[PDB]
Image 1: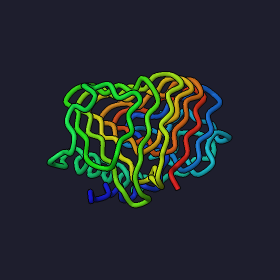
Image 2 (image 1 turned 180 degrees about the vertical axis):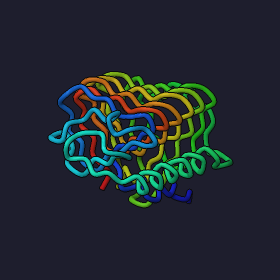
Image 3 (image 1 turned 90 degrees about the horizontal axis):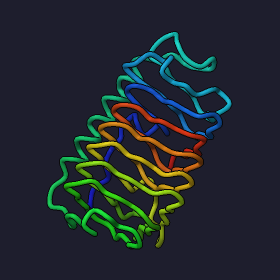
Length: 216
């Protein structure tokens, strides 16, 4: 069995970025949100969009924000450690599965690697036990097309799924994603896409009327 990727303090966030969070009103985020080292002004969410707390490094930001620089610094530090831990895992079980396109597949537990961009153009399933772990290592971008849905089967849980991407993630309109995203650059969601997972970006997270829920 493959070890969990430990998120440390970042586990407490639904969205954590380094250069902000952009949004087309109205999104529905469940869980805490934060950005650092950038100013809290870079968080373009209103308070009715977030059920949880909005954290800022400073006095700027949405009206309900809490200022807490040391927690955001630890969180961001922990996200970096997680990203490096995930990208650093060795001996994949798969390499270049589907040649970079994985529509229709059922993915069983393990460590998967892609040395290019990964596309998800049609529905997929992630299947395994309540304690199985999946780590997806993607050296380019990650794309998912509109209305694509990731289904979990067999007791598989979103909190045990990790997607590490060296490039940007793009989730298409109406799509539904499962798992923790650790991106080295951005994560960008389109109209009414949803995610059950965490969006951890080393640049920005962009949203357009999305539903974002932290995995239980």
